Structures are given as structure tokens and as C-alpha cells.
Image (tube, helix red, strand yellow):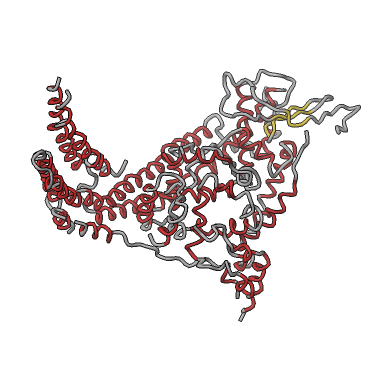
Amino acid sequence: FLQGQKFCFQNLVHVLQDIRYQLSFARLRNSDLVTALDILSTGTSLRLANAPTSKLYMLSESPLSTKQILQTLHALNMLIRIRLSLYEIIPTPFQHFTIANGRCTFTVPNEFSVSLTTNSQDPKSTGISFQWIVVDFQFHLPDFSSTP
Amino acid sequence: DADISSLSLSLDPEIIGGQNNFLENNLQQIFQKIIQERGPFRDLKEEDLQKELQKESIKDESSAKSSETENVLEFATLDSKRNVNDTEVESMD
Amino acid sequence: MACRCTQLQDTIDEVATQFYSSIHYLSSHHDFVSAEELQFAQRDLAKDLVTKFMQIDTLINQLPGISTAPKHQLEKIKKLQNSIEEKQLERKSLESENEDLKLQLAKRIETFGRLSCVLFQP
Amino acid sequence: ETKWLLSKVPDDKSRFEIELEFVQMLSNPWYLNFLAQHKYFEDEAFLQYLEYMEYWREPEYVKFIIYPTCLHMLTLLKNPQFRNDISRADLSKQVNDEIYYEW
Amino acid sequence: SAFPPPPPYYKLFTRENIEKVISNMEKEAKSLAKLFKKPSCLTSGTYQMFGDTWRLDEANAIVGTSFTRVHDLIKIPRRAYELRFLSRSLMLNFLELLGIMAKAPEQFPSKVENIRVLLLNLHHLINDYRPHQSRESLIMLLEKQLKHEESQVELLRTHNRQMTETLEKYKSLDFNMEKEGDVIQQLKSSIKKP
């Protein structure tokens, strides 16, 4: 009411939106929040900061790290073999081993590795070894095998 | 009460409630930082296991370094930010 | 939901204009008018405008905190902290008592699952 | 200490007043487009953008009235290196006023 | 607006002046830094109810009785029956206007001023009770958080014993492998069989 009214003397936008009373109700919510604590994380969140258009455009950085990635490995570590516990069909001669990537080595011929990049929660029927990607191809051919 | 700290998740319950798992959400994120695709990542599994050890061992053993605080330290990033413009990334295709 | 009281403004402040819109019906339409139909419009002016106000009274009955004891309500919230906040440590402790072992046990399943493959490819 | 004396037009009332008084201005959808001139952007202007972060903290944030400026702070917080807060954002930002204000 | 609205403080924002802080803070181990220090702040106006008190003076009839309510029984009948009486009286006041209007409409339109005085007896008490709604809503949410807590019971309690028994079932001894011990034993439990 003090300096803020002086701020209202400018271009009268701040508050570029037509809404204004909602901010006052939010102030009442703040006075209600004075009795709170814990927690500070609940402060602006009670007003839902940056939720007005988070669903909209934006871009956002937010680094993805670190051990969270390991958890994903465990997911695959559980997931792939389950798909193999199900379907499968077939394609032997293979030797499945779910460690980070689904391994598929050969004898004289070559090794291959696999990992899906779509979705995880869809096995069983209509989950017959569907999504996959080649991860590398380090062939073990006895005559040539340097693999540039 | 402390439960209010979780209320944002309740606020999330009214919305998208976190995108969570997705192809890009793990893989495209993996393209950032470590490593070079899942190929480097595969051998980076055990390296990540070692990273959990001694790299995480340094829980606390240093000066408070409060002199850098606070908004000034926030202003310190501006050098790297202005330096970031020089990247001119990337492929010409 | 909350702030039912604001709705009362719609039942009053908005309704108050209706008495003003009614003014034309009581005079001006009688000139260049059939006309008896206007009387029906008058009847609702004599009726509905009252009834919603009566509804407001029911809305008064519906107003939350009928006990009207906020000082006690905050104490109720104190009991709510006495419950919830003590629950939090337990409910958080649960996952630690759970998945921390469940992962490893699942790995123990993983071992047998792997050794099944030996039988699968003798 | 000479720099404070050098701040003739500057210095001013400073404090809680003028800072928030400027922070409120970002909400205007074209105003960010105006920030694409010389008044301030990625230059030394960024020093202001980074300095203000303490306002997100409790008590100081209690003083904040309209969320929209803080959401603009989220915009600069978004990849300011690119169109999220540098090439940003044409008149399209006004469309956000047509939706977020509704709820 | 400001004069001009862009900040003039950028000149003070030079990075080397921040570098001064490293020197000045240790300078007194046993000047311009204040410029980088966090700003002073006004109240700036915590007062609010006083405007409502002025609204009481803005005329406040039965609203004073509503103040009397500010100590079923208790204040409830005062906020109920008397308010209903204010509503019925509010209906009675229309006859001050439209009830006699065509006959010299001078004082009669001004009779509505009494009604606008009665508005002080109405919505203002609603505003008086308005903060209490925040209490009711906060209480409304506070056990909802308890419900989000309940979901963990809704799932983990199920995962527990099931995981344990399934370990005890076909897995039986899931520790039976004992890592390396499960190597040759995989033959001893199978290839040895005949």
C-alpha cells in the first residue's frame, strides 16, 4: 500500500494480467502461511510459483545427475530379462545377459548389444521383444576385428 | 505443518504430476553429461559404481567460504554465461 | 472448496441490480404496449428475488466453521501436527526398511534367473 | 569508494522500492521484447538479473505481490542463452495473459 | 515509472567491485560493499483492518451488533437471525423507493442511501468472517496430506510380505547362490543330478 501504490502510478502493469484480487487473496494466504514452517519449500509453492504456464512453452535447463542414471540401469536390469522371460521367440543361438545392455554374443562371428528407447511398461503379449536399439557392434571375426 | 512441504506434490496432483519416465527423459538426458551414448555408458556403469565410493566420500572437510556469498556468487556465473556465446554450436549438416 | 461467503455477493450485489432493471417493467412498458404478461414478470420480482435471499440463509447454515472458534481450530491443527508430523518419520522410514533390501533380494532372484539360462542352453 | 560518487543519477532510493518496482515490469509481454535493445539484456544487464535471486527466499518473497514477475524470473532462469530468454518472445507472451489470468 | 525505468546500477555491478569484497571482508580480520548488500525493506503496510474500521465510520447499524458478536448459543444467533432480519428489512427498504416513486421523486431516490448504509451491515461482516475461510481450507488440505501419506501404506505394506514370501517361495533360499558358490553348484544342483 505504501511504495506499491507508487508502483501503480507508473504504466499500471505488473500485473500485466487483468487479474489482481487473486494476488490479494494470495497475500491473505501468506498471512496464513506465517503460522506455518515447516517448510520454506512450501512457501512460493503454496502460491504455485512458475505454475501459471509451466505446461505451456518454456524450455528449462535442470541437469540430470547423477546416481539417478544408475537406477535406470537397474530398471533395464530387471526389465529386459522379463521381456525375455516372456517373449522371447527366439532367436537362438543367443546368450542373453541383462547387464546395462542386453548382450548377444556369438562364437567365431560377433558380439552385439541392445537397449530400448521408447517405453518399459508394455511387455507380455504385444511385448514380444518389441522396442530395441543397437548399442554397438564389436564383431569378433577371427580374420578381421579391429573395428574402426 | 511439515506436510505442507509435500503439498506441492498435491499441487502437482492437480496437474501433470511430473513427466517421469520417457525415452528422451533418460536417454536424451544421458546424451547430456556422461556419456558418449549408451556405448560409453555401458563401461561407465562400473565407473559410476566407483564414483559412488571415494567421490562421494568427501561429505565435509573444508572452510565455510561464506565470503563468496551470496548474490555476488550469483553474479559470478555471468562470466561463464557471456563466455557461453562463443560456442557457435554445432553441426552444419 | 473454500470462501463460500463470496458467493453470497453474487446472491446480493448482483441481485441488487435486478431491482433496478425491474424499474422499466413497472412504468415504461405500460406506455407503448399482452400487457398482462408484464404482471407475471412482476410476480417473480415479488417472489424469486426473495427466495434466493432465503437460500442465502441456508447458505449461512452451510458456512464452514459453524462452531466459530478459530482459536480452537488452530489447536485442532496442533493435534493434526501431533498426528501427521509423527506419522511422517514412520512413513518415510518404511521405504528405507523396504526397497533397500528388496533391491538386493530381487538381485537374489536375478541370480537364479541367470542360472536358469544355463539349463536353457546346455 | 569513488564509484558511489560516480553514481550521480544512480544510487537513488535503492532498497525495497525501486528494485521491486523494476522487477514488476517484466510481466508486460512486449517489455521483454523491449529488453532486446540496449537498456539491458545479456551484457552488464545480466548482473542485475543474477543479483536479484535472493528475492526468491522467504520473507523477501512475502513482500512480492504479483507472481507473474517471478515467473518472468523463471523465464530468465530458463535457457536465457536461447529463445527462452534472449530471442524471447514476440507478442506470443500476451497469449499467456489470456490463459493464466483466467486461472 | 522510474527515471528512466531501466536500472542505473549496472555501473556499480562491475565484477571487479565484487572482487573488492574478497579484499574488504578480510581487510578487517581483526566501503562500497554496502552497495552489493541486501536492500532495506519497509513494512510496508501491515495495517488492513483499520480500513474496515473506517468503513464502519464510512456511514453501521446492526454491524455494531456484529461487533458485539466478536467476543448453538454464543454469537451465532446474532450472525444468523439478526442478519436474516437485515435481509427482510432490506426487502422492506425497496418500498422507500419503488413503493412510492411517481409521487414527487425527490427524497425517495435518496432513501436508497439508507440501503447503501445498510451495505456496511452486510458484506463487511462477511469480510470479517472471510479469514476464517482460510483456516477452514487449510484444515481441509492438512489431512489430504495425511492421505498422500496413506498411499505409502496403501502400497508398501503390500510389497513387503509379498516380496518376503516370494523370496521364500520358488526362490526359497535366494541367498543359496552365495554369489561364487552358485557357480559350480549350478552344475552340482543339476549336472550332478542323474
| Whole-percent x, y for residue B69 in the image | 59, 65
Q: Is residue E106 above or below residue A110?
A: below
Across and down, in percent, residue E23 comes to: 66, 73
- Who's the residue at 31% across and 48% down the image? E139
User: Quarter of the image holding residue C63?
Assistant: top left
Q: Nearer the viewer, residue D87 or B71?
A: D87
Q: Position of residue A146 (x, y in %)?
A: 88, 33
Q: Residue at x 71, y 40 (%)?
A: B41
C35 lies above or below A8: above
Is residue A62 visible in the rendered structure shown here?
Answer: no
Q: Is residue E44 left or right of residue A110?
A: left
Residue C54 placement, left or right of B79: left
Query: Which part of the image, by quadrant, shows the C terminus of chain D?
Result: top left
> Residue C21: x percent and y percent?
21, 34
Residue at position x 33%, y 48% from top?
E138
Tell which of C65 and B46 is nearer to you. Answer: C65
